[PDB]
Every structure is written in C-alpha cells, then in structure tokens.
Image: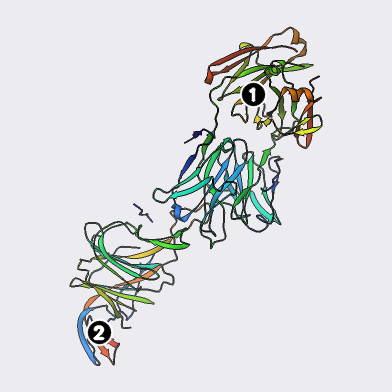
Amino acid sequence: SQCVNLAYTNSFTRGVYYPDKVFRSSVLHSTQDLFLPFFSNVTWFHANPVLPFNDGVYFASTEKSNIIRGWIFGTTLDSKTQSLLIVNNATNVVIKVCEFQFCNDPFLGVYYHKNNKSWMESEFRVYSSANNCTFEYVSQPFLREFVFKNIDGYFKIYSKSALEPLVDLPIGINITRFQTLLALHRSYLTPGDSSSGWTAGAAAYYVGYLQPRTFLLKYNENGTITDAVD
Amino acid sequence: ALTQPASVSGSPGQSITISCTGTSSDVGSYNYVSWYQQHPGKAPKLMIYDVTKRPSGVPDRFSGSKSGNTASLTISGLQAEDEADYYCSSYTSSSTWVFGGGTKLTVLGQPKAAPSVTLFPPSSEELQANKATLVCLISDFYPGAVTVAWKADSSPVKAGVETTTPSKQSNNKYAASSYLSLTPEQWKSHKSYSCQVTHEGSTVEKTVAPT
Amino acid sequence: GAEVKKPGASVKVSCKVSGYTLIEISIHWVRQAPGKGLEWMGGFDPEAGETIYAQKFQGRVTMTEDTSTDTAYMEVSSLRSEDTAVYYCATGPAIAAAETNWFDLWGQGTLVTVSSASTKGPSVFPLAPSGTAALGCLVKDYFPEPVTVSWNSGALTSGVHTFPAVLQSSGLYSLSSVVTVPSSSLGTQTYICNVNHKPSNTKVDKKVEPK
C-alpha cells in the first residue's frame, strides 16, 4: 500500500440553485425542494473530518491555490460498498464510482517526475484498492461554491446567487458521508528532507446542510434574481 | 581535479581552514560546492552543500565560503571528534561532479614528531633469485601525513614504487613503509639509491649503495 | 554484499532507496579505492533530465533504475585491478527549478575486489643489520591477508615493529617486520623471525644474521 497517516460557525443568505427544474419561467414560482436555510449554522473548517451528507450539503471555499481538488462520497467508504470520487486536474475533471479501499487520511499526492520535467498527482494515497468500477465521467474541471444532492439514484451538482446546474450523474449508489479531497506535495530539495513531510498552504472550507423548505424564486428573463423563505 | 592541502592540524578549541582551489569550470561558475567528512571505515558525511548551507544536525562550527575559484571550509572550536578526512566537491560546466584530493585533519594531541627512516638494501639471497627489493620503513611521526620519493643517483624514480598508507602505532604515532622493486642489473648499475620522506615540510633522506 | 571478481569480468552493484521514490530523486555513484580519495563516477543532472557520466567511465559504466522495487543499479564492465574500491550510491535533488545541487551518500557502500591472485605462501628474506641496530624479515609476495610475524618463538617482543602490508601491482602482498636491538648483542644473540601464513598453511623460520 501507499497510505500515509497525517470548530467555528457562520451564516449567510446563499445556497440557491435552480430548483431541480430546467423549465423556463419569468415570474415568481413556489417550490418545495431541498434548500439551505438563509441564516443557518454553517461550519467553518480548517485543514479534515469525514462529514455526514444527510440530504445535501452546501460547500464553498475561497482557497487561492489548487489544493482542494474534490470530494469522496459514499457510505462505509470501504471496499464493501461503492463510493463516489471527484478529482480536478489542471486540465480535466474525473468522476468515478468504484469499491475504493480508501486511506484513513486520503490526499492527492503531488510529486516530482524527473523523467518528464513535471509535477504529477498520484491517486494512490487516496485509495489502496479500486475494483468494480461502474461509472467514469471525464470533462473540463469545475469564491467557488457547490451544492451536492443525491436523489433517485442521481448525484446532482450546482456550482458558481443562483448556482447554475453543473452536471448530474446516474451514480445509483447510497451516499451518507463525505470527505474533502486535498492535494499535498513533497520534494527532495535539502539533504535532511523527510519523505513523510507532505504539505500545502492552509485550506479551509464552509459546510452547510440542505433542508426541505418551501421557497419562492423570482425569474425575470433567465437567472433567478431574488428568493424568499419564512 | 580540485586542489586541497594534503594535511592540516590544529589544537582543540582553535580554528582552522581547508581551501579548495578550482577553476572557472567549477568553483568559479557555480554555487554548488559540497564538503564531506570521513572518519576511518565510515561513509563520507555531507557537512556543507551549496557553498554555505549545512544539513540538519551539522553544528554551526562548520562554515563554508567561496572567493573566485577558491572554496573554503572553516572549523571553529576544534573537537577531538573533528579529526577526519575532508573532501570538497564541485559541480562542473560539463554537468559532472569532481572531488578534491582530500585533506587529512589532525586535532593535535601530542608534540609533533619527525619520522625515523630505515632503508634496507636488497639481500644477497633475494639477488640470487633474480629480484631486488629496497625496503624503506618509516616510523614515529605525528601528525600522520608523509610523502615518499625515491632517487636513483640524483634522478627521481617512480616506476616500481609501492607505498602504504600511514597507520596508527600503539604509542599513537604513525608508521608507513615504501618498497622499490628493481632488477639486479639496475641495482648494481647505479652508485646509490635514496628514500626521501617529507613530513611537516621537512625531509629525512636515507641512502644505500651496492658497493 | 562484497563482490570478488577476476580481471576482465563485470559487476552490478545494487542500492535499495527508501523514503522518496527513485522518480523524484537524483542518483549518483561515487567510489573510493582503499587508502585513496573519493571519485565521482556519474549522476543525474537536474538541468539535463538524464544521467551524466565522467568521461573516464563513459562506455564502461551503465546506471539503471527499477522504479518497481525502488532499486538503483550500476554495472561496471571489463573491470581491472584499479576498480577495487567501495562503491557508494548517493541521493540528490532532481528539480532543476530550484537552485540547489548536491548528493548525499545513502548507505555504507559495497566493497568490490578485483584480483587475479590465488593462494600463495610467502618467500622470506633477511634484512641484515648494518648505539642500537635495526634488523628484520621481508615477507614477500603472499596472498591473501594475513601473515603473522613473531621473533624467537615469542621470547622477543620489545622493540618489534611489524609494518602493515603493501598490495603490489601483481595482486600479492608484502610486509616487513623489524626489531630494534642493542648493537653489542649482534654477534652474541640469535634472532629468528617466525612467519605464519594460515591461508596457505605455510610456516617459515629464518635466522637474521649480520652481513
């Protein structure tokens, strides 16, 4: 194997996405969906814990570098069940569903490759094993805020108020917990360097949870402009 | 090759410097000078890299500097454990690395002593075997750094010379030996042969003749 | 482990590097002949992206790497007796964008001996003496180490200096053993050196006697 062994709260009126509907409209429209309460208790994390998923999550981060690369979703996060794994390269996004034998403290290891002049990332250090892969999606990579919901076998994603729909995925798997996927690097540059010294800039992310609440969405010509809940 | 002094000595607590004279192809054009320490029987240890930087664990008594084509290692507050061989190393404009000849470093623990030199001519028993060996035995010198040169009459000889590295005696001084392999015709043809030992800039010579 | 090789053969030394993997590290090889200094053979230049060899070794040394096992290899071919040395692998940086370059030796090296010599007992010659006097025995052309020298079956021990052996070009060893005795006793006291070479089961007793 390759695995390595390595709060504050807030509140704001964001976390609005097109209401799981792709219908065009130009007036106010009510909706009973899974939404984020406007002045709810958001948790401010420093990095890294396995967080519950519940019915949805609000995720946002202002991290300057390319340290936060994605997330892992699933139940036991073991080889016993299938899990979701989103990874963002500088050029691509990669979404796979397999039976990942995840590491206790997963991270996307960044290392120097002397024969290519380049830095590269290793999905080892994230999972020691990966079998029974049923789904693989590849396209361009994803303040950066996301909404994740897993309903009717589909995993739906909105990004950027008014979070536009990013993509939704016929995953068809149960998702109860998730963890943020960090990119760590290491280099042999001083005679005393330690191979265990994986490091990166300080990374922090906001996590909220979605609630089943009636909302009102104001459309003018395209994007949702205002919103309302009580 | 980079040039270092053969040997350097100092008393405990004092400072010493070892110089490393290169050329424009290595010390003059790059900041990649390393210094290595070697105790008897053990692998060289990196003491300085990139002219001035020390790896974690190396004490601050070791420091490096560079001027022109000359790099220097300086040791402050000499310790008994600092007695070792020191090698400098430099990156070259051929993308290679080169080493200096090494500097033997002695932390003085007794008065300096000049070597005793004994020279034995070829024995008659050996001559009758169509072989001739001159034996030059060097003992009781401190610090343990010498050089040997042979002379046939007044001319230098290098072919047929085998010299041993110095080895600590029981009384903490050093000993060494040098052998000159001759043919019986060469031996009887000249009037004399000489063994010359140089220690602390002074020379002790011994001479033997076939007559 | 240590390697013994006839002249003209080839050897392949290994080095298993833990910690960082071989792909993110520059590998260097240095060697040191017994009693001599360090010699750089070749290494990975970060700016070049490949391995550079000292021109003395191009065509006869090849370095390769097994990224699976993280083992670094170096193969020397058509090896001669001058290749007897301890061979050290060394680790250095590979990122050319940083402005650090150096190599740190990894392990305690592997010894590689190249010799065509086989078991041979010594021929012993007297070193006749010329206040006190030096006399001894020349223990010549034996293999392998060691030989033991004593005087008068152990009765004589004071003033005895057995010098370390020299390794000559033929691949054989020679040493000398000298005893310093009063000059007055030269005609009255008998001096016999006892040579014992266990590797060849040879024992020689020889009386050293004034010329």
Marked residue chain, label 2: A
Query: Mark 2 vs mark 1: same chain?
Result: no
Q: Are circles 2 and 1 on residues that touch, CB within 8 Å?
A: no
Are there few (<14), some (14-19), or many (20+) residues within 10 Å of tag 1?
many
B45 lies above or below C209: below
Most foreground residue, B159 or A161? B159
Most foreground residue, B74 or C7? C7
Q: Amino acid at mark 2?
A: Val
Q: Quick one: SS at disc 1? A: strand
Measured as percent of width and height from the top left, residue B209 is found at 79, 22
Measured as percent of width and height from the top left, residue B95 is found at 59, 55
Marked residue chain, label 1: C
Tell me the quadrant of the picture where the C terminus of chain B can be found. top right
Measured as percent of width and height from the top left, residue A215 is found at 23, 84
Residue C161 visible in the shown view: no
Name the mark nearer the viewer: 2 or 1. 1
B65 lies above or below B14: below
Q: Quick one: SS at disc 2? A: loop
Q: Amino acid at mark 1?
A: Leu
Most foreground residue, C203 or C7? C7
> Which disc number belongs to residue C175?
1
Measured as percent of width and height from the top left, residue C209 is found at 71, 11
Query: Which residue was labeled with disc 2?
Result: A229
Q: CA distance from mark 2 to mark 1?
A: 101 Å
Q: Is residue C145 left or right of residue A34?
A: right
Give the residue drawn at x 62%, y 26%. Answer: C165
Q: Is residue A224 left or right of residue C147?
A: left
Give the residue drawn at x 40%, y 74%. Answer: A62
Colouring? rainbow
